[PDB]
Image (cartoon, rainbow, N blue to C red):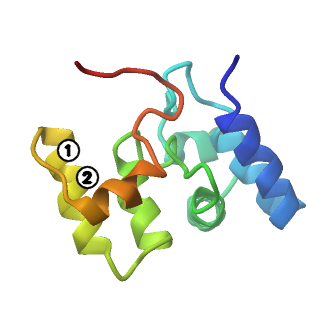
Amino acid sequence: YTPSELEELQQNIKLELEGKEQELALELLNYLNEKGFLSKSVEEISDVLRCSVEELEKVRQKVLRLEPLGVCSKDVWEFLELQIEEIYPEEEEILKKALRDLKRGKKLKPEIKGKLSRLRLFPLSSSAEK
């Protein structure tokens, strides 16, 4: 079985929205590497694609909020931070401390475990510990 995270995000975008906005988003997520994150900054990518930085940002954000989140937009670990601010903006601090504890290594809470369980810092990757 192959990963359908990226493809799922593309379709979702064209679904909720379409036109020029979707175009910009695709471009940003189009100039990325097989690592799960854009190989070039948004500024440069926007200059090469012939698009205003500010504009590309707004569209990139609206599309980044989609599922999966814009891991390439912010980053691999940043995907969680933005995911909360967008999904659960009320528990931004809650998940913020959790994602930081799990990323740096630590214990997790019972409620957070389930909240983060629905997500994963390895959307386009795979890894686990024993």
Q: Are marks 1 and 2 in contact (CB under 8 Å)?
A: yes
Q: Is 85 positioned to the left or the right of 129 in the image?
A: right
Kindly tell me whether residue 15 is visible in this rendering.
yes
Question: Where is the C terminus found, in terms of image quarters?
Answer: top left
Q: Which residue is mark 1?
A: 102
Looking at numbered disc 1 in the image, what kind of residue is underneath it? Answer: Leu
Q: Position of residue 91 (x, y in %)?
A: 32, 76
Q: Nearer the viewer, residue 18 or 97?
A: 97
Q: Residue at x 31, y 54 (%)?
A: 113
Secondary element under disc 1, as helix, strand or loop, is helix
Q: Position of residue 16 (x, y in %)?
A: 82, 66
The image's mark for residue 99 is 2
Looking at the picture, does residue 100 appear above or below residue 89?
above
Kindly tell me whether residue 17 is visible in this rendering.
no
Q: Residue furthest bottom?
A: 90
Question: Where is the N terminus found, in terms of image quarters?
Answer: top right
Q: Position of residue 61 (x, y in %)?
A: 57, 63
Q: Residue at x 35, y 59 (%)?
A: 81
Looking at numbered disc 2 in the image, what kind of residue is underneath it? Answer: Leu
Q: CA distance from mark 1 to mark 2?
A: 5 Å
Find residue 19 and report its image quarter.
bottom right
Find residue 47 and report its image quarter.
top right
Q: Position of residue 110 (x, y in %)?
A: 24, 60
Q: Is 64 positioned to the left or the right of 119 in the image?
A: right
